[PDB]
Length: 281
Length: 281
Image (cartoon, rainbow over all chains, first blue to last red):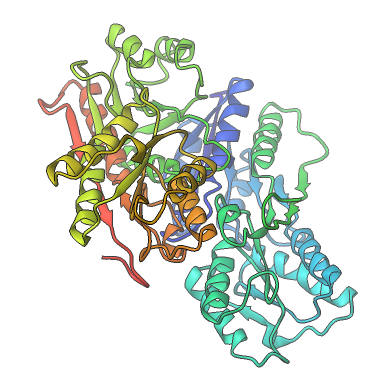
């Protein structure tokens, strides 16, 4: 054993409000350290198909396993490591009946809970700022919305489901499009797939003279640092990134040391954070 | 050579808007990789005096050098590595005539520039939300303010220099204290030592019915992601964290490989980011 776990992360877009690198990596580093392991960061290949670096690290004997993040459908990195029978844990699922060790956050449960909360306040025209169809995480989160709306038997309007990049600009543009609707057809609540989008929605609401919360409710996703300081403070879905980090290391170390548990699929639940004038419940 | 550089970072307080771990570490990882080196993260000891982990990593031969961040005055880690004659580069100075290799951002120049800008708009009552006296970075940044005010020959009021923790709560409290002053004595502009503080100031201004920018100008520090999305968007001092990361690796690799340059002190300049209704200049 080299007592080292290889890790890499996708380049953070300049303009994204959330950076869970700190929560995830810090957590892994401290957890690994407790059991005498080190996390070895290596350059990420934006073209996930290029697995050369993985190939190199394996035969160099510099690591005993890998932790993968930013998992897409049919992830080439997952395919490769599976073929090589090399130890690894993916932080995020990929392809339904594709088998391997993983830790993930129940995105679906997150949005479902958020939507149920809005319905519980009496909201009936709820829209969502979602992501493209090729996004695994996006579909999970969107699914929760569909389920909650279906269960409450509320209309699921195609005009209320806008797909695009998770940016401030897109969030704002899509919301302005929705606010262009008359009071009768305009949604009273908007669910977004990340806080950056929610901020754009807040900007759009402000531009159109609507009071956030009262006239237009907004719930984001990933409870990025500082969203709590906005006015009104932003309600959002928080994911247990630190715990997920700890679970990844914990599961990979067990696999690397030959004592793989029967529970190689760890699904963690997110928490809905509702914020009012001050303090969240 | 082990071709590995050890690095560790202080635990990010829950509630801080900026996380330069991503900019700094990502940059180091990619730079090291280009010259065949890896960055090896190890658990940070909040009690900087406890240098055991450094002692262990050196004789284990697992690293050829270290990069240090969160440098305080008379930093025990710097003292130790200096005694051990072990390669290291500090990201941040410590103790004036204390000698060693380092890369740092000219904090003083950052605030001076910010204050000069405010004076250039005609501001004469400018206050600052600063940090405690035992903060090396705090004193550097505060120094720039004093210099600019002194140069423009404007009053340097003790009532306008409030020291405390760089939090939202403190920034807000200190600003409300300042806004308690009548229009005649109230400052027209506020400089803060980090964006978290500036956000609190923005919250205070909002609570007291003042238009940010027009009635009360605010300039923060570290241009954390998303401050650009606030209303009004927040002007702030940006530091070249990625470049600093690259310079650290670059300087340490040279020292580790026996070809230490004569320029072992690298001081980088920050940039003032002025933002208006949309787009920054």
